[PDB]
RNA sequence: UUUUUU
Protein backbone atom coordinates (compact mmCIF):
# COMPACT_ATOMS: atom_id res chain seq x y z
CA UNK A 1 0.00 0.00 0.00
CA UNK A 2 1.81 3.05 -1.33
CA UNK A 3 0.58 6.04 0.63
CA UNK A 4 0.62 9.47 -0.94
CA UNK A 5 2.90 11.17 1.58
CA UNK A 6 5.07 8.07 1.78
CA UNK A 7 5.62 8.04 -1.96
CA UNK A 8 6.16 11.78 -1.69
CA UNK A 9 9.16 10.90 0.48
CA UNK A 10 10.19 8.01 -1.79
CA UNK A 11 10.28 10.67 -4.50
CA UNK A 12 12.30 13.05 -2.40
CA UNK A 13 14.94 10.40 -1.54
CA UNK A 14 16.29 9.39 -4.96
CA UNK A 15 17.11 13.05 -5.69
CA UNK A 16 19.36 13.65 -2.67
CA UNK A 17 22.05 11.09 -3.56
CA UNK A 18 25.45 12.87 -3.55
CA UNK A 19 37.00 8.77 -11.60
CA UNK A 20 37.07 12.50 -12.12
CA UNK A 21 38.86 13.64 -15.26
CA UNK A 22 42.34 15.14 -15.38
CA UNK A 23 42.93 18.72 -16.50
CA UNK A 24 45.91 20.98 -16.96
CA UNK A 25 47.68 21.37 -13.61
CA UNK A 26 50.54 23.71 -12.65
CA UNK A 27 53.60 22.78 -10.62
CA UNK A 28 53.78 24.19 -7.07
CA UNK A 29 57.28 24.83 -5.69
CA UNK A 30 57.43 23.74 -2.07
CA UNK A 31 60.24 24.07 0.39
CA UNK A 32 61.65 21.39 2.59
CA UNK A 33 63.83 21.81 5.63
CA UNK A 34 66.49 19.29 6.58
CA UNK A 35 68.42 20.67 9.51
CA UNK A 36 68.53 20.48 13.29
CA UNK A 37 69.92 23.94 14.02
CA UNK A 38 67.47 26.28 15.82
CA UNK A 39 69.09 29.17 13.96
CA UNK A 40 68.22 27.35 10.73
CA UNK A 41 64.58 26.69 11.51
CA UNK A 42 64.35 30.36 12.56
CA UNK A 43 65.74 31.62 9.26
CA UNK A 44 63.58 29.10 7.42
CA UNK A 45 60.48 30.49 9.10
CA UNK A 46 61.39 34.17 8.63
CA UNK A 47 62.29 33.34 5.04
CA UNK A 48 59.07 31.47 4.24
CA UNK A 49 57.18 34.39 5.79
CA UNK A 50 59.04 37.09 3.81
CA UNK A 51 58.08 35.02 0.78
CA UNK A 52 54.45 34.58 1.79
CA UNK A 53 54.07 38.34 2.19
CA UNK A 54 55.61 39.28 -1.15
CA UNK A 55 54.64 42.35 -3.13
CA UNK A 56 55.98 40.94 -6.42
CA UNK A 57 56.31 37.12 -6.44
CA UNK A 58 53.81 35.18 -8.52
CA UNK A 59 51.00 33.13 -6.98
CA UNK A 60 51.92 29.41 -6.91
CA UNK A 61 55.08 30.43 -5.09
CA UNK A 62 53.43 32.37 -2.28
CA UNK A 63 51.18 29.39 -1.98
CA UNK A 64 54.24 27.21 -1.49
CA UNK A 65 55.74 29.61 1.01
CA UNK A 66 52.53 29.24 3.03
CA UNK A 67 52.59 25.47 2.75
CA UNK A 68 56.08 25.73 4.21
CA UNK A 69 55.00 28.03 7.05
CA UNK A 70 52.42 25.42 7.86
CA UNK A 71 54.89 22.51 7.48
CA UNK A 72 57.88 23.96 9.27
CA UNK A 73 56.43 23.08 12.68
CA UNK A 74 57.41 19.41 12.58
CA UNK A 75 60.77 17.76 13.23
CA UNK A 76 60.81 14.83 10.77
CA UNK A 77 59.38 16.66 7.75
CA UNK A 78 60.11 13.99 5.13
CA UNK A 79 56.91 12.07 5.86
CA UNK A 80 54.79 15.20 6.22
CA UNK A 81 55.87 16.41 2.77
CA UNK A 82 55.28 12.85 1.53
CA UNK A 83 51.76 13.23 2.97
CA UNK A 84 51.68 16.44 0.95
CA UNK A 85 52.68 14.36 -2.08
CA UNK A 86 49.89 11.89 -1.36
CA UNK A 87 47.24 14.19 -2.84
CA UNK A 88 47.33 13.33 -6.54
CA UNK A 89 45.06 16.15 -7.73
CA UNK A 90 47.63 18.97 -7.64
CA UNK A 91 51.42 18.67 -8.21
CA UNK A 92 54.18 19.56 -5.72
CA UNK A 93 58.00 19.44 -5.82
CA UNK A 94 60.62 18.93 -3.12
CA UNK A 95 63.45 21.49 -3.48
CA UNK A 96 65.58 20.26 -0.60
CA UNK A 97 66.85 23.69 0.40
CA UNK A 98 69.82 21.93 2.06
CA UNK A 99 70.11 24.85 4.45
CA UNK A 100 71.60 28.31 4.09
CA UNK A 101 74.95 29.49 5.39
CA UNK A 102 75.70 32.11 8.03
CA UNK A 103 74.95 34.86 5.55
CA UNK A 104 71.20 34.96 5.44
CA UNK A 105 70.80 35.06 1.66
CA UNK A 106 72.31 31.93 0.16
CA UNK A 107 69.96 29.13 -0.45
CA UNK A 108 72.49 26.38 -0.69
CA UNK A 109 70.97 23.50 -2.57
CA UNK A 110 72.27 20.31 -4.18
CA UNK A 111 69.39 18.99 -6.27
CA UNK A 112 67.10 20.31 -8.97
CA UNK A 113 67.74 24.07 -8.91
CA UNK A 114 70.01 26.72 -10.49
CA UNK A 115 71.86 29.86 -9.49
CA UNK A 116 69.74 32.03 -11.75
CA UNK A 117 66.76 30.83 -9.73
CA UNK A 118 69.43 31.52 -7.29
CA UNK A 119 68.84 35.19 -7.86
CA UNK A 120 65.10 35.55 -7.99
CA UNK A 121 63.86 34.74 -4.48
CA UNK A 122 66.65 36.60 -2.90
CA UNK A 123 65.50 39.01 -5.41
CA UNK A 124 62.06 38.09 -3.98
CA UNK A 125 63.42 38.55 -0.49
CA UNK A 126 63.43 42.19 -1.59
CA UNK A 127 59.74 41.76 -2.24
CA UNK A 128 58.28 44.13 0.31
CA UNK A 129 54.93 45.66 1.16
CA UNK A 130 55.44 49.35 0.36
CA UNK A 131 52.35 49.90 2.51
CA UNK A 132 53.83 47.96 5.42
CA UNK A 133 56.17 49.80 7.76
CA UNK A 134 59.76 49.13 8.85
CA UNK A 135 59.71 47.04 5.68
CA UNK A 136 59.43 43.94 7.87
CA UNK A 137 56.65 41.61 8.96
CA UNK A 138 56.88 41.91 12.71
CA UNK A 139 55.53 45.24 14.06
CA UNK A 140 58.07 45.56 16.89
CA UNK A 141 61.18 46.27 14.86
CA UNK A 142 64.11 44.84 16.81
CA UNK A 143 62.64 41.34 17.10
CA UNK A 144 63.85 39.31 14.08
CA UNK A 145 67.57 39.74 14.84
CA UNK A 146 67.01 37.47 17.85
CA UNK A 147 69.03 34.55 19.19
CA UNK A 148 67.23 31.20 19.31
CA UNK A 149 69.58 29.59 21.84
CA UNK A 150 67.34 26.53 22.26
CA UNK A 151 64.81 24.79 20.09
CA UNK A 152 61.90 25.47 22.40
CA UNK A 153 61.50 29.22 21.68
CA UNK A 154 62.04 28.58 17.97
CA UNK A 155 59.15 26.13 18.09
CA UNK A 156 57.05 28.59 20.09
CA UNK A 157 57.64 31.33 17.51
CA UNK A 158 56.71 28.91 14.72
CA UNK A 159 53.58 28.09 16.72
CA UNK A 160 52.67 31.77 17.04
CA UNK A 161 53.11 32.50 13.36
CA UNK A 162 51.21 29.38 12.31
CA UNK A 163 48.45 30.08 14.84
CA UNK A 164 48.11 33.61 13.55
CA UNK A 165 47.53 31.80 10.29
CA UNK A 166 45.16 29.18 11.78
CA UNK A 167 43.02 31.84 13.41
CA UNK A 168 42.77 33.69 10.06
CA UNK A 169 41.70 30.59 8.35
CA UNK A 170 38.08 31.19 9.45
CA UNK A 171 35.90 33.72 7.64
CA UNK A 172 37.52 32.27 4.60
CA UNK A 173 35.45 34.00 1.89
CA UNK A 174 36.85 36.37 -0.75
CA UNK A 175 35.24 39.67 0.09
CA UNK A 176 37.13 41.38 2.88
CA UNK A 177 35.14 39.96 5.77
CA UNK A 178 36.17 41.96 8.69
CA UNK A 179 37.10 39.43 11.33
CA UNK A 180 39.97 41.44 12.80
CA UNK A 181 38.17 41.95 16.12
CA UNK A 182 37.28 38.28 16.54
CA UNK A 183 40.80 37.35 15.48
CA UNK A 184 41.90 39.78 18.21
CA UNK A 185 39.57 38.21 20.80
CA UNK A 186 41.08 34.81 20.06
CA UNK A 187 44.60 36.24 20.15
CA UNK A 188 43.76 37.72 23.54
CA UNK A 189 42.50 34.41 24.90
CA UNK A 190 45.53 32.62 23.45
CA UNK A 191 47.37 35.19 25.53
CA UNK A 192 45.25 33.98 28.45
CA UNK A 193 46.65 30.57 27.52
CA UNK A 194 50.12 31.93 26.83
CA UNK A 195 51.41 29.66 24.08
CA UNK A 196 51.75 32.77 21.86
CA UNK A 197 53.78 35.82 22.85
CA UNK A 198 52.67 39.39 22.39
CA UNK A 199 56.14 40.00 20.94
CA UNK A 200 55.47 38.24 17.62
CA UNK A 201 52.36 39.77 16.10
CA UNK A 202 52.37 40.28 12.36
CA UNK A 203 51.21 43.28 10.35
CA UNK A 204 47.41 42.86 10.06
CA UNK A 205 47.31 44.18 6.47
CA UNK A 206 49.77 41.52 5.26
CA UNK A 207 47.84 38.97 7.32
CA UNK A 208 44.52 39.70 5.57
CA UNK A 209 46.38 39.46 2.29
CA UNK A 210 47.66 36.07 3.44
CA UNK A 211 44.00 35.20 3.96
CA UNK A 212 43.04 36.41 0.47
CA UNK A 213 45.89 34.23 -0.81
CA UNK A 214 44.67 31.24 1.19
CA UNK A 215 41.24 31.41 -0.48
CA UNK A 216 42.45 32.13 -3.95
CA UNK A 217 44.44 28.80 -3.93
CA UNK A 218 42.57 25.53 -4.24
CA UNK A 219 44.83 22.91 -2.77
CA UNK A 220 46.37 24.80 0.13
CA UNK A 221 42.86 24.59 1.64
CA UNK A 222 42.69 20.90 0.79
CA UNK A 223 45.91 20.53 2.75
CA UNK A 224 44.27 22.51 5.56
CA UNK A 225 41.30 20.12 5.44
CA UNK A 226 43.55 17.08 5.74
CA UNK A 227 45.56 18.81 8.46
CA UNK A 228 42.31 19.41 10.37
CA UNK A 229 41.06 15.87 9.79
CA UNK A 230 44.23 14.41 11.25
CA UNK A 231 43.82 16.96 14.05
CA UNK A 232 40.28 15.96 14.91
CA UNK A 233 41.36 12.29 14.72
CA UNK A 234 44.17 12.51 17.28
CA UNK A 235 43.36 12.38 20.98
CA UNK A 236 44.50 14.72 23.78
CA UNK A 237 47.81 13.23 24.83
CA UNK A 238 50.09 14.39 22.01
CA UNK A 239 52.29 17.23 20.67
CA UNK A 240 51.40 20.91 20.96
CA UNK A 241 50.88 21.63 17.29
CA UNK A 242 47.89 19.30 16.86
CA UNK A 243 46.48 20.65 20.07
CA UNK A 244 46.54 24.19 18.71
CA UNK A 245 44.98 22.96 15.48
CA UNK A 246 42.14 20.95 17.05
CA UNK A 247 41.53 23.69 19.60
CA UNK A 248 41.05 26.29 16.84
CA UNK A 249 39.14 23.71 14.85
CA UNK A 250 35.76 24.10 16.51
CA UNK A 251 35.89 27.73 15.40
CA UNK A 252 36.80 26.71 11.85
CA UNK A 253 33.96 24.21 11.32
CA UNK A 254 30.25 24.58 10.60
CA UNK A 255 30.75 27.80 8.63
CA UNK A 256 28.32 29.31 6.12
CA UNK A 257 25.70 26.75 7.09
CA UNK A 258 24.55 29.26 9.67
CA UNK A 259 20.84 29.84 9.00
CA UNK A 260 20.48 26.06 8.65
CA UNK A 261 21.83 25.62 12.25
CA UNK A 262 19.86 28.52 13.65
CA UNK A 263 16.78 26.62 12.46
CA UNK A 264 18.12 23.51 14.18
CA UNK A 265 18.78 25.39 17.41
CA UNK A 266 15.69 27.62 17.74
CA UNK A 267 13.16 26.33 15.23
CA UNK A 268 13.21 22.63 16.06
CA UNK A 269 15.31 21.63 19.08
CA UNK A 270 12.86 23.60 21.30
CA UNK A 271 9.75 21.78 19.91
CA UNK A 272 7.25 24.53 20.54
CA UNK A 273 3.60 23.81 19.70
CA UNK A 274 3.46 26.24 16.79
CA UNK A 275 6.04 24.07 15.20
CA UNK A 276 3.05 21.81 14.87
CA UNK A 277 0.76 23.75 12.63
CA UNK A 278 -1.26 23.47 9.47
CA UNK A 279 1.66 23.31 7.05
CA UNK A 280 5.07 24.07 8.42
CA UNK A 281 5.53 20.29 8.18
CA UNK A 282 6.72 19.95 4.56
CA UNK A 283 9.76 22.05 5.26
CA UNK A 284 10.33 20.00 8.46
CA UNK A 285 10.25 16.90 6.28
CA UNK A 286 12.92 18.49 4.13
CA UNK A 287 14.78 19.47 7.35
CA UNK A 288 15.13 15.82 8.33
CA UNK A 289 16.04 15.07 4.71
CA UNK A 290 19.06 17.40 4.97
CA UNK A 291 19.70 15.80 8.35
CA UNK A 292 20.02 12.35 6.78
CA UNK A 293 22.16 14.03 4.07
CA UNK A 294 24.31 15.57 6.76
CA UNK A 295 24.91 12.32 8.68
CA UNK A 296 25.38 9.98 5.73
CA UNK A 297 27.54 12.71 4.23
CA UNK A 298 29.51 12.82 7.43
CA UNK A 299 33.23 12.68 7.03
CA UNK A 300 33.54 15.88 5.02
CA UNK A 301 30.29 17.27 6.31
CA UNK A 302 31.41 19.92 8.84
CA UNK A 303 33.63 21.27 6.05
CA UNK A 304 31.73 21.82 2.83
CA UNK A 305 32.40 25.54 2.83
CA UNK A 306 36.11 25.07 2.84
CA UNK A 307 35.66 22.09 0.65
CA UNK A 308 33.80 24.13 -1.95
CA UNK A 309 31.52 21.47 -3.35
CA UNK A 310 28.24 22.63 -4.88
CA UNK A 311 26.04 20.31 -2.77
CA UNK A 312 25.70 22.82 0.07
CA UNK A 313 23.43 24.52 -2.32
CA UNK A 314 21.23 21.63 -1.21
CA UNK A 315 21.64 23.39 2.12
CA UNK A 316 19.75 26.34 0.68
CA UNK A 317 17.98 28.36 3.38
CA UNK A 318 15.55 29.56 0.74
CA UNK A 319 13.25 26.59 0.29
CA UNK A 320 12.66 26.84 4.09
CA UNK A 321 11.72 30.54 3.94
CA UNK A 322 8.60 30.04 6.11
CA UNK A 323 10.22 27.89 8.79
CA UNK A 324 13.50 29.78 8.35
CA UNK A 325 11.76 33.07 9.08
CA UNK A 326 9.88 31.77 12.11
CA UNK A 327 13.04 30.25 13.69
CA UNK A 328 14.74 33.65 13.12
CA UNK A 329 11.98 35.95 14.39
CA UNK A 330 11.93 33.86 17.56
CA UNK A 331 15.73 33.91 17.94
CA UNK A 332 15.49 37.66 17.37
CA UNK A 333 13.26 38.02 20.43
CA UNK A 334 14.51 35.16 22.66
CA UNK A 335 18.21 35.53 21.93
CA UNK A 336 20.22 38.69 21.71
CA UNK A 337 22.50 37.76 18.88
CA UNK A 338 22.71 38.76 15.22
CA UNK A 339 21.22 42.19 15.96
CA UNK A 340 24.30 44.03 14.63
CA UNK A 341 24.04 42.84 10.98
CA UNK A 342 21.58 42.11 8.13
CA UNK A 343 20.86 38.43 8.46
CA UNK A 344 17.69 38.32 6.36
CA UNK A 345 16.44 37.34 2.90
CA UNK A 346 14.20 38.86 0.26
CA UNK A 347 12.44 35.52 -0.27
CA UNK A 348 11.11 35.89 3.31
CA UNK A 349 7.49 35.73 4.55
CA UNK A 350 6.43 38.62 6.77
CA UNK A 351 3.62 37.00 8.74
CA UNK A 352 5.61 34.09 10.16
CA UNK A 353 8.22 36.54 11.36
CA UNK A 354 5.44 38.54 13.03
CA UNK A 355 4.27 35.31 14.57
CA UNK A 356 7.71 34.31 15.81
CA UNK A 357 7.64 37.65 17.61
CA UNK A 358 4.15 37.23 19.01
CA UNK A 359 4.72 33.59 20.03
CA UNK A 360 8.07 34.35 21.65
CA UNK A 361 6.70 37.39 23.47
CA UNK A 362 4.49 35.22 25.75
CA UNK A 363 6.80 32.74 27.46
CA UNK A 364 3.89 31.41 29.43
CA UNK A 365 3.52 28.73 26.78
CA UNK A 366 6.74 26.62 26.99
CA UNK A 367 5.27 23.38 28.31
CA UNK A 368 7.07 20.13 27.56
CA UNK A 369 5.82 16.58 27.75
CA UNK A 370 9.27 15.60 28.96
CA UNK A 371 9.58 17.33 32.32
CA UNK A 372 5.82 16.85 32.82
CA UNK A 373 6.22 13.08 32.73
CA UNK A 374 9.53 13.50 34.61
CA UNK A 375 8.50 15.28 37.79
CA UNK A 376 4.74 14.56 37.86
CA UNK A 377 4.18 18.30 37.68
CA UNK A 378 0.99 19.75 39.13
CA UNK A 379 -1.37 22.29 37.60
CA UNK A 380 -0.50 24.47 40.59
CA UNK A 381 3.18 24.48 39.65
CA UNK A 382 2.26 25.11 36.01
CA UNK A 383 0.27 28.25 36.77
CA UNK A 384 2.92 29.25 39.32
CA UNK A 385 5.78 29.21 36.84
CA UNK A 386 3.36 31.00 34.50
CA UNK A 387 2.99 33.84 37.01
CA UNK A 388 6.79 33.87 37.09
CA UNK A 389 6.89 34.34 33.31
CA UNK A 390 4.29 37.09 33.71
CA UNK A 391 7.31 39.23 34.57
C1' U B 1 24.42 31.86 -2.87
C1' U B 2 27.52 33.77 1.24
C1' U B 3 27.31 38.07 6.30
C1' U B 4 26.95 36.35 14.97
C1' U B 5 29.06 34.52 20.09
C1' U B 6 31.94 30.65 21.98
Image: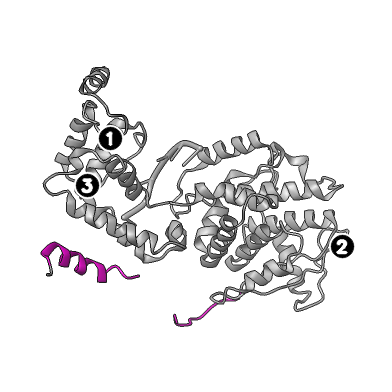
Circles 3 and 1 on the same chain:
yes
Determine crowd level at label 3: few under 14, some 14-19, many 20+ residues with C-alpha closer than 10 A: many
Mark 2 lies on a secondary structure that is loop
SS assignment at label 1: helix
Local secondary structure at mark 3: helix
- Where does label 3 land, which residue? A323
Quadrant (top left, top right, bottom left, bottom right) of the C terminus of chain A: top left
- Can residue A84 be seen here? yes
How far across and how far down the image is residue A350, in percent?
16, 41
Q: Which residue lies at the image location 66% right of the left edge and 43% below the top edge?
A: A133
Highlighted range, magenta:
A3-27
Quarter of the view holding residue A63: bottom right
| Quarter of the picture holding the N terminus of chain A | bottom left
Q: Residue at x 54, y 41 (%)?
A: A183
Q: CA distance from mark 2 to mark 1?
A: 76 Å
* Residue underneath mark 2: A101
Against A50, residue A91 (above or below) is below
Query: Does the image show residue A29?
Result: no
Q: What chain does badge 3 belong to?
A: A
Chain for mark 1? A
What residue sits right under mark 1 in the picture?
A373
Closer to the chain start, of discs 3 and 1, is: 3
Amino acid sequence: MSSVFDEYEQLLAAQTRPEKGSTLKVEVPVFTLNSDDPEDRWNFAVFCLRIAVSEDANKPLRQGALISLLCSHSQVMRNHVALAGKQNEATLAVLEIDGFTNGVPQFNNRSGVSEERAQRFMMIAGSLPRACSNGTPFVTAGVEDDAPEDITDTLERILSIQAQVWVTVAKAMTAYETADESETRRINKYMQQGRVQKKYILHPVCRSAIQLTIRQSLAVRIFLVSELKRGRNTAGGTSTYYNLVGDVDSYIRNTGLTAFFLTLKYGINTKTSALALSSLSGDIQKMKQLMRLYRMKGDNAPYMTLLGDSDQMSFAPAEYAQLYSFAMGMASVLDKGTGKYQFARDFMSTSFWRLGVEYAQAQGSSINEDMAAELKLTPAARRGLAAAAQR
